[PDB]
Amino acid sequence: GAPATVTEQGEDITSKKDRGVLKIVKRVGNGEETPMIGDKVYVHYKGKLSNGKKFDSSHDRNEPFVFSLGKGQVIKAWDIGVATMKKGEIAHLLIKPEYAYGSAGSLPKIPSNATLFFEIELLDFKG
Ligand SMILES: COc1ccc(CC[C@H]2OC(=O)[C@@H]3CCCCN3C(=O)[C@@H](c3cccs3)NC(=O)C(C)(C)NC(=O)COc3cccc2c3)cc1OC
């Protein structure tokens, strides 16, 4: 399924090239531009542990998730990953714990040393 496909064909978008964040473009977005650090970004997402458990989505309550990019407002993988996305793009990310919740986890939902999977849709971004 979707996580396995990321392993096989995802691009390693980390600076250290440690496969900590792997990305596939599932739906191409519009234009050329991708958000800059400091931009306000609007997304929909679905997340889970890579094994399929602990599913959560912003579409549950059909309300976009908004954050400023590169301002420590989300896990590192999202600051890295969303920065690469075009408006209208849907991406899949597979994330090792070093780029997510690490050894601490986010208990009880997210265990220590958890690998995560996300589907993210970049709806819009603004200066
Ligand atoms: C700079 O580092 C951090 C900055 C902020 C946080 C707080 C958690 C933060 O959530 C996230 O960063 C990620 C990506 C954005 C969407 C929510 N996140 C999730 O991991 C998902 C997951 C879904 C499935 C498995 S994990 N969390 C949720 O969907 C739920 C469980 C609903 N919780 C929240 O969304 C809580 O609301 C938040 C609001 C802002 C930032 C974060 C969470 C943790 C950070 O590092 C550990």
Image (cartoon, rainbow, N blue to C red):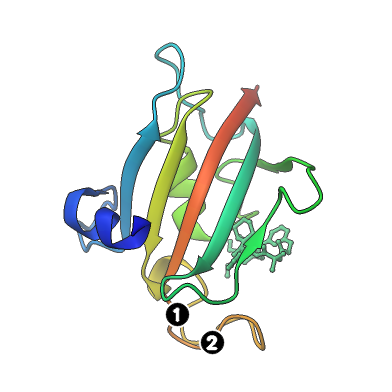
Query: Residue 40 placed where, x, y %?
Result: 67, 32
Q: Is mark 1 within 8 Å of ligand 1?
A: no
Whether label 2 touches label 1, CB < 8 Å = yes
Does residue 112 sit above or below 28 in this rendering? below
Residue type (three-letter) at the residue carrying disc 2: Pro
| Residue at 43%, 84% in the rendered image | 113
| Residue at 52%, 75% in the rendered image | 101
Name the quarter showing ligand 1: bottom right
Label 2 Cα neighbours within 10 Å, binned few <14 / some 14-19 / many ≥20 = some
Quadrant housing the N terminus: bottom left
The image's mark for residue 24 is: none
Residue type (three-letter) at the residue carrying disc 1: Ala
| Closest to the observer, 67 or 90 | 90
Kindly identify which residue carries mark 1. 114
Kindly identify which residue carries mark 2. 111
Q: Quadrant of residue 18?
A: bottom left
Quadrant housing the C terminus: top right
